[PDB]
Structure formats: structure tokens, C-alpha cells
Image (cartoon, coloured by chain):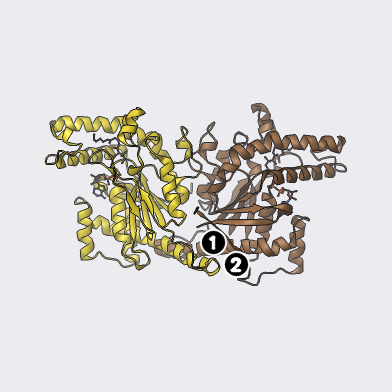
Chain colours: A brown, B yellow
Amino acid sequence: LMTPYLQFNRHQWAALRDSVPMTLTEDEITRLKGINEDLSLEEVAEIYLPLSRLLNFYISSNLRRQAVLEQFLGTNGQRIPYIISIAGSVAVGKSTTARVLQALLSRWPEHRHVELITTDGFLHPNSVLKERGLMKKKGFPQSYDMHRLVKFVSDLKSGVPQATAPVYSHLIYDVIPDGDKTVAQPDILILEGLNVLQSGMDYPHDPHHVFVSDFVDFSIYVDAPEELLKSWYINRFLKFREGAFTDPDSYFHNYAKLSKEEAVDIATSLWNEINLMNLKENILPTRERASLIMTKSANHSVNQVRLRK
Amino acid sequence: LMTPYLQFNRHQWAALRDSVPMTLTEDEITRLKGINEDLSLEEVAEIYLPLSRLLNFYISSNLRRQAVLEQFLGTNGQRIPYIISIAGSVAVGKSTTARVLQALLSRWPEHRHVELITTDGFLHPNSVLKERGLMKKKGFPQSYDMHRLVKFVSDLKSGVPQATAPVYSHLIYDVIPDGDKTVAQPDILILEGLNVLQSGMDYPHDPHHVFVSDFVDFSIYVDAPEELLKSWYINRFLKFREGAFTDPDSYFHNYAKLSKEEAVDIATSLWNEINLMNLKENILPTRERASLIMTKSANHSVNQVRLRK
Ligand SMILES: Nc1ncnc2c1ncn2[C@@H]1O[C@H](COP(=O)(O)OP(=O)(O)O)[C@@H](O)[C@H]1O
Ligand SMILES: Nc1ncnc2c1ncn2[C@@H]1O[C@H](COP(=O)(O)OP(=O)(O)O)[C@@H](O)[C@H]1O
Ligand SMILES: CCCCCNC(=O)CCNC(=O)[C@H](O)C(C)(C)CO
Ligand SMILES: CCCCCNC(=O)CCNC(=O)[C@H](O)C(C)(C)CO
């Protein structure tokens, strides 16, 4: 049956890809690989360049509408950033997807200044999660300072000249105590996190009545089947453990003393008991709120793009 | 502090009507007076013509974008209506606002076909409300078949060739037995109802995960102080009562049989015990989710307009 999404067929996707010259210079190819050494350049050419080009159509149409309204309404021409959000399971590739889209979108002269903010920064710090008995519930709704996350995007959509977000580090598994990131009226702000499509219903312990989505222009849910997500999560955990072999400041220091087999069992249980329950209860149900659903397969290659009609 | 809204006072909003020349036609005037005899044409020319022109800019921007996307999407796809929703208290003037905008938006050659659907039709019938003890809660979240309403707008946004809504009559105070209304791909659909800005959080008894708002391009919340809403509610009730003098099939015949004074007492209790409580608990908290908040003062005169930046 018909749904609110069109699924791109290969001729529509190819025409999008081929609509512009947008293959990259050598230096740009180098910086892309620096985002993630496992990123395929074939994916960049077949998937991420066209997806960034698709977004440009939306962003550009919005700038023109803004010019038309400022003339009509007689307003002072104030800059409002276009906000793109990126949702999905832990370990689906939200960060990589977001960093790739930041780099590619910045190539278009109409919107060169692209910022990226993760919702991880808005987690309550470990001290606080401890106080509340939620250290096993990191990434669940009760673990976020949701009111502050909404205020951040709300302030941006208010035309504030600067806004400040707290910052989180996966390497030390916590919010950086004085590591705040200040942004100033970018053309585009990408908001990356598992909870960007969540709403007041997900926070009954402390309700809010205006949602992140109410301040977001375009949202992407990055989707993938459970088994792939689990293996991606375990592999990434093993990578951090490896890092910890030589870096004493890694939070994975003690995991690097275990056998690999035991480390795998731990990661497996973290996935099963925390991130997978979080997916099923809180993340996956938000999926049909997205502007666009990008589905991933083997080796992270995107096999389906659905866009709201 | 700056907010997410451009704020216009009446002087500033009315000043828009010259910014782009516009005057009502002769046929339009007759249509308008047939919509509401108490509706001022000056109020139409000063407030609603500029509002309609605002909306045309949004709608036209969308149509232009759609044309551009069609370059790679192709033209085979189904026509999707632009959906405008109208929220606010019982008796604020949603229906009047909707019907006026339907009349005025028909002007433009870009979008001549304009349908109007009220969420009233998606109320559970009185028999069902009686089963569930909800008869004193008509208009509260539990009194709606919300799943059916989300599906209706979802279907429209899926490109169905036709979609069908149930219809309600204030005259018989119930859903009409076999009175369903079918719409066929209009250019604009106006959805009018107190609950159009509500979400799953408002339906904890039977939650939904994609909201009405997720299928709405542009939302208006019509706002006014409680004391005016009360007066407008009571006056309307007395007008329904008069209509029932010569109409014993009106549910208001029950009140036509009573003295005016006692009828006013009843109407006032219904306001205070049902609609005012609904406003405070369920309607007003959704106001900040609107694209535009239009505020009214004495005699329905608009004194402030707020539009999302
Ligand atoms: N497009 C991709 N190509 C190859 N590997 C990827 C891709 N996206 C993500 N990954 C890998 O999958 C894992 C999860 O990605 P990450 O961006 O950290 O997910 P998230 O931010 O959603 O938690 C990481 O190990 C990352 O290197
Ligand atoms: N713009 C207006 N000018 C004059 N009277 C109005 C206006 N809007 C609404 N009314 C009156 O106020 C009452 C409530 O309006 P209605 O459109 O029935 O409200 P709702 O649909 O919100 O319940 C009605 O008696 C209506 O005639
Ligand atoms: C050094 C400790 C390793 C355990 C990591 N915990 C988990 O994967 C379970 C909690 N989830 C997370 O830590 C997720 O990465 C987060 C909620 C921050 C979303 O990006
Ligand atoms: C006895 C016949 C008139 C009773 C009117 N009821 C009320 O005003 C309370 C219930 N609310 C309503 O009937 C509202 O009009 C509705 C919820 C349908 C929103 O358009």
C-alpha cells in the first residue's frame, strides 16, 4: 500500500546523483577518509554526494522563501540556521553520517558554514546518573537533560547570536567538565543523536510540550537491522579496547586487561541489556517521524532511501 | 529575551495589506457574509487577507520546491495536498477562521481546490462515549478516535486518490450516522480542531507515535483570554438555541424549552466544567507548537500575530 514516504528507485537516485558535477578533489577525498578510515569512497560517490545534493534543494528552497518573507513582512533580515537532525540506534553510524554530511554540505557556496552538535553532550554527567541509579540507562530518556537540549535548538531558532552546548567524550565515557562548544549563527546546524525524534511522551518523568523536532527543518533516521547493529557495536567496542592497549587515559583501560573473548561477552551484554532495549523501547518507534529514512546493509552500504512525499 | 516567533502588533499586521495590493471581490463579500454574519469585512481585509497572502507564499515556495524535486523524481507521483491545521479553545473561532481562509485561498490559480475537514467528525459517537462514561469529556483526548484521525492525514500525505472522514453535527450533538465526507486530492486541505497540535503524550491511554502535526505543513493556533472565550461560547449557545425555536430535530430544542436565563446558566456550567478544563489541561499547552499564533481581543479583533522564524 501507499505510505507517506516515497522510496527512491534507481533512476530517480541516479538522476539526483548526476544532476551536478560534484566529484571531489584529492584533498577533499583525503579529509573524508580522515573522518572515518573505513568509509568507502564508492559510498561517498553513490550515496553521500547525492544525499547532500538532495538536502541542498531543501536548504536552498528555504533560503529563497526566507528572502521572499522578509520583503513581505518588513523584517530586519535576521539569520536563522537550517537544522538537520540525524537519529537512529546506537552504533548505526549517526556520527559518521553527520560528519560526512557536514563536510559535503560545506562545499555549496550558499551554505558554507555547517556546525555539528551531538545530543550526547546533553546527557546528565556520570555523577548525576550515579545519584539517580541510571548508570545502566545512559541514552535512555531519563539520562538526558532534555529541557536544556530543547532550549538549545529553540534559542538557535530564536536568532540568538551564540548558543552554547555541553560536550561529551566516548573515550572518557562522560560529559567534558569545561568542554562546552559555542556556535554562532551557522548556515546549517546538524544535530546528531538517538533522541532527536523523541517527544514529550518519551519523558513522562519530566514532560515537555514543544519538541526537538519543532525546531528542526529536516530529519534523517539512519536504520539498520538488529544483527548488523550488534556486530557494528561490538566491533567499535573492540576498536576502543585496542586503543586502550597504549592509551592510559582511555575509559576502556580495564577492558584491555580482559581476554578478547571476555571483552566480547561484555560488549555483547551492553548491547543486549542497554542499547538494544533502548532501541526497541525508545528509538525505533520514532522512526516514522523522520523526513527521510536511510537504510543500511552489509558493510554500511545504504540500500534504501525513503523520503516524505 | 528573543523568542522563536516574529511578533506583529495589529498596526504592523494590518500594514501588510498594502505591501502587496489586495481587495475583496463582490462575489467574495457575499460568500464571506454567508459564512458568518457577524464577521466584519474590515477585519477580513485587514487581518485575513494578509494571512492568506502569507500562506500563499508558504504554499507557493512548497510548490516550486516540488517542481524542482520532480526533475529527478519525475511527474508520475501522486498529488499531495498542502495541509494547514487550525487549533485553539472551543469557541475561539477556529471554524470561522478555517472557512474564511478556505474562501480566500481559493483566489490563487496555484491552489483553487481547498477542502475543509473538522476533527469533530473523529469524536467517538455519543453511544460510545456513554459506554465509557466520557459524555462529560467530549473534546478531551479520550473522546477521539485519534488513530483514525492520524490515518486520515497520513493517507492524504501518502497520495491516496481519495480519503474519507466521518462528519459531526453540532445541531444533533453527535457523529452523523452515514454522513461521511470524501475528499479527492485537493490543492489545500484545512484541518480544523482543538486537538491538531496534540501528540502521543496526550493519549497515554492508547498512544500513537506519529502525530497529526507530522502530516501538517502549517499550523495556526487562535488564542484569546478565557473571559472572552466564555462570552463567545455562551453567545454561540444562545444562537444555536434560537435556531432550535423552529427546529425540533436540534439537540438545542431541549434548551429552547427553557427560559433564556436558565439556558445561560446551563451553557455557563458546560463551559466551566468541560471546555475550560479541556482548554487548560489539553489545548493551551500545545500552543507553542504552532507555526503561527493569532491572538484575539474584544469583538474578535486580532491584536497580535506571532510567526515562527
Ligand atoms: N558509512 C560507514 N562506513 C563504514 N563504517 C561505518 C560507517 N558508518 C559507521 N561506521 C562504523 O560503524 C560504527 C558505528 O558508527 P558511529 O558513527 O560511531 O555510530 P553512532 O554515532 O550512530 O553511535 C563505527 O565503528 C564506525 O566506524
Ligand atoms: N472573526 C470573527 N468575527 C466575529 N465573530 C466570530 C469570529 N470568529 C468567531 N466568531 C464567533 O465566535 C463564536 C465561535 O466561533 P466558532 O468559529 O464556532 O469557534 P470554534 O470553531 O473555535 O468552536 C461563534 O459564535 C462565531 O460566530
Ligand atoms: C567505557 C564504557 C563502555 C560502555 C559503553 N556503554 C554503552 O554502550 C551503553 C550506553 N550507551 C552509550 O554509551 C551510547 O554510546 C550513548 C548513550 C552515549 C549514545 O551515543
Ligand atoms: C447539549 C448540546 C450542546 C452541548 C455543548 N457541549 C459542549 O460545549 C461540551 C463538549 N464540547 C463540544 O461539544 C465541542 O463543541 C467539541 C468538543 C465538539 C469541539 O468542537
Q: Which mark is residue B249?
A: none
- Mark 1 belongs to which amino acid? Tyr
Foreground residue among A35 and A149? A35
**Disc 2 packing (10 Å; few <14; some 14–19; many ≥20):** few
Mark 1 CB in 8 Å range of ligand 1? no
> Label 1: which residue?
A58
Mark seen at residue A11: 2
Residue B187, image quadrant: bottom left
- Residue A7 at x, y percent in the picture: 56, 58
Q: Which chain's residue wears label 2?
A: A
Q: Are marks 1 and 2 on the same chain?
A: yes
Counting every numbered tag in the picture gives: 2
Frontmost of labels 1 and 2 is: 2
Q: Residue B102: give x, y in percent of width and height.
A: 31, 57
Tell me if I can see residue A168 in this picture: yes
Residue A266 higher or lower than B43, as above or below: above
Q: Quadrant of the rendered structure where residue B170 is?
A: top left
Residue B23 location, x and y as percent? 26, 65
B38 or A277, which lies in front? A277
Q: Residue at x 19, y 41 (%)?
A: B240
Q: Amino acid at mark 2?
A: His
Are there few (<14), some (14-19), or many (20+) residues within 10 Å of tag 1? some
User: Can see residue A74?
Assistant: no
Q: Is residue B268 left or right of residue A267?
A: left
